[PDB]
Each structure stands twice: as C-alpha cells, then as structure tokens.
Image 1 (cartoon, one colour):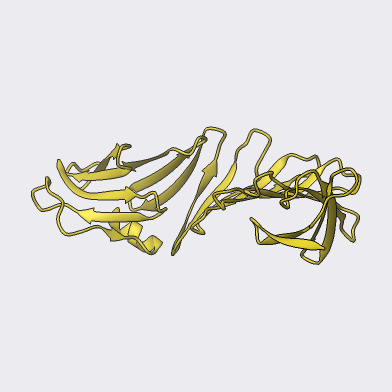
Image 2 (cartoon, rainbow, N blue to C red):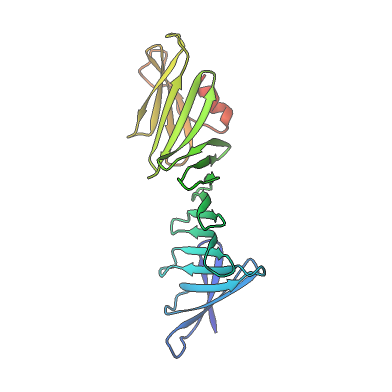
Length: 246
C-alpha cells in the first residue's frame, strides 16, 4: 500500500509502494488536519502535494528530491499571490515568512537549529524593518536595513551595537558619550575571534565573545590590563550584558 516517510518541519508523507502506469507515485499528507495530495516521479516521498483550506486558500507542500528541505506555502484563493511560506532546510533552520496583500515579504522569522531566533517584522519594500534576536535567556532589539541588522543595548552613556550583515557576518561596536578620559569606554572588534575588547583609561577591562553557539560570554582582564584572568562567563540575561557595559 503506502510507505510513511519522515520529513523536515515535523511532517510526514505517505508514498505509494509502487508506481502507476505513467511511472508516477501517489503522495498523501495531513498537515494540521488539512489533507494534501499529489503525484511524484520519485519513489522516496519527495515531490509536490496540494490542498485547499476551508477559506479557499491554496496550500502547497514541496519536498526536495533528497528529502532535505520542505516548503509549505499558502496562497490566496486563485493560487496566484503568496500569503505565507514556511521553509525547513537540511540544517533544520526554519524560515517563516508572511506576505502582504500584494505578495511582498512583510515578516520573516528565522529559527536557528539551536532554537534562537531572528524576528523581522514590519518589513517595507526597501527591505527595512524592525528586528529582534531571541537568545537563551534574553532578547536583543533593533532595526533591519537592506545592509544589516543592528541590535542595540544601552547602559549609561554607553551604546553597544551588534551588527549582522546581509550575508550573516557579525561585527560589534561600542560608543560612549562620556567625556572623562578616566571612565569612558572604548572598544576594538576582532573579527577573527568574534571578540569585542573593552578598554577604560588605556587598559583592557573585558572581552565580550559573541560565539558561534549564539551566546555572549564576558571575561575580565587582570588589573594590569594585559592578561585575561579567571574564565569566561556566559551571559544569561540582559541585565548581565548591561553590567558588562558599566
């Protein structure tokens, strides 16, 4: 009869055990109680399934040839304009996209494999919008442009800016409007190690590491200002970032 196949995005598809006279396989899936069906020229569960919501919206599920990726799309009732698109890629990263009345991207939520998120909302036609990074224990807020995402933490006269470029490269900068040379913070960014080193009064005070695990760690320097001391501590809430900027 049929073979159950496990799919990215918490879905399953039933594929026929044998092909039809055209050599094609039948596909069946139920996604949140909606029944979808289709035919494929592959036997592994890949291909295209379609259905129609109670409100007449068209639904299409596209499963890539190697089963690595699923795309779940909802359209207006004539099938021409997108309403939403949900993509799980082979790295299990989720892209959840909303479109406006004219089919232009208006919201995009990215869920990384570790569960952290980039939330882009109010997206305009120039690709600008509001931005939020949702990390384990805290959230960073800022803006999106076509050039970069900029997330901002403020403490006293210090502004910390985490940039994520259009290509995904992270850089961090720090700016202090403090005028006194004794207490003002400055900072240097090391792209090779994703580390921001803070300096006060010509001595290094701490390293903030922005890790590949989507965490931030802080480590102090010795009173001299040259050697790191102790070991790095992972930030677990926004107040601890603010503390590192004091």
